[PDB]
Amino acid sequence: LEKFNVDLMKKAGKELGLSLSPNEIGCTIADLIQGQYPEIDSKLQRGDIITKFNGDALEGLPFQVCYALFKGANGKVSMEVTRPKPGSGGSGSLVPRLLRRNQYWV
Image: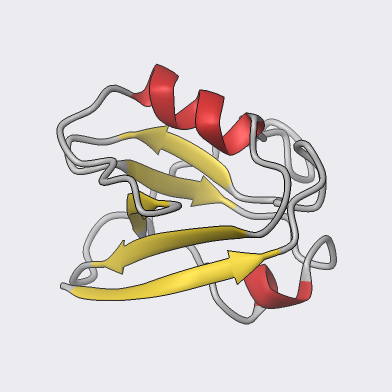
């Protein structure tokens, strides 16, 4: 299980383009809208889980809190994402046949 930090300038929910999902250790990135942020595009990906956010362990906490801080982010946002082994996200994927990027964006 790899883990790195993603820091980017946050302007109250916008280019963050990183659809989060309900996880036990944090929020599994269900998706991300590339082109929104450079760092994110070069940092976040599909199949990771944000277990840390601005020096705040998102492990054990619900998703409501994560969605809130991620949505209430504004002024440099450093999120430690965990990229576990492959397996989930290949046949069914977290994002169904909704739209281009129809996802839960913060």
